[PDB]
Every structure is written in structure tokens, then in C-alpha cells.
Image (spheres, helix red, strand yellow):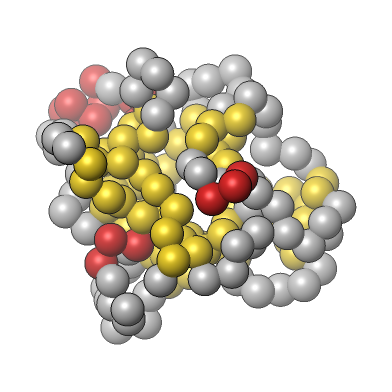
Length: 154
């Protein structure tokens, strides 16, 4: 079971420094932005990372939600990334949840983080180019895959 402990405003970047944002259609995407542009787009770029205590410690347990949104919490249900219409809950009774990820520092890589699904072991949040877009996906982990590494500014 998980219990919510604390929350921090966060900006998330992939390894090419593209900023995670939520677009008009509620999709999580990455794009290039100058800090001035990131500030100007604060409502679409500011996330809340909420840390939870876990009765079965396996890594820093977090939800990721949109700050300037009524209720948009990141989910990997069915191995598909979406925002569900809910807030980070105070308690979660199960040992796995489609909205809980384990945030882990990457050994040997300065300040980088990975986010592993609590529901689907060995699956991580990743940035994947599709057509001309860079999208947030869930994918299975080759060692040192840079597409599953992020910087978190808080």
C-alpha cells in the first residue's frame, strides 16, 4: 500500500533537453523551448511529482500530475500513456498501480532519472519520436538506453 507524503513542482526534460508538456488534446509530448518559452508555457509544462511511502519499498514511489489542471494524472494502464481525470490520491491500497512509478537515479549518469512502472516491471517512461513529434511512451528496457533517461528540475 502507498500513502502520499509530499509534492514538488517539476519540469521534466528528455536527454536532448526537450521539455515535457501537455498539448491541446491532452497528449504528453516533448519539444525544444527556451527558459523564456518554458516560463511562457508554465500551464502546459509544470508538473507535480508526488512522493508516496510504500509498504514494499522498491524505489521512490511517485505520481506525475499536471499542475495547472483540475485533475490530470499520468497513467500507464494497458501499457498506454494517458492522463486520467483524477488527482493523486492520499492512499492507494494495492502494491501496484497504473499511476505509480518508481523514480530512480541512473548510476554513472550525472543527475539523470528513470521512471519504472509499478504495474509493469521492466517498463519505463520513454521519449519516442513518431513522425515529427516526440512523445511520452511506456517501453520495455539494452543497458544505457538514453530514451528512458530524464532530467527533473524542481
